[PDB]
Length: 93
Length: 93
Image (tube, rainbow over all chains, first blue to last red):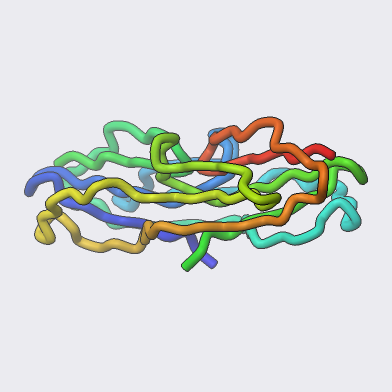
């Protein structure tokens, strides 16, 4: 199960990547540009003991992921903002 | 497609409802207690013209929903906090 995402083109030299990451903290998320690819990695935290009695129902699943997007030469990631359970990454030519 | 949720029991007189609502704004969300049921309604905003050329890929779907939970008599909703794409509702006996 990989996060849903959207990819938009704001114009020909710009892209906006939106990744659905509800419940993810900034420290669990990493973005890096390596060998011309943009890698977005979610590594969900060191486990926690969970009393299964306290859990009545668990419909929300959170699993580590890695998304990879080839960047056109010579594209740069300008910012990555985490807001409202969404990771927004602007990619500029 | 209804939002995923979790339901936890913090102890016997307390519950925590967590609803996955990434990208939802506070103005699109409503919680109300009516006839002993807790109703959580998401009504996604007045449409916007969307240039389908700007959309390369749209994996993130956002659809209006309504979740309903019977409250034990005499339970109250203490707060509803929207944070990190999650709606957290504490329900107290």
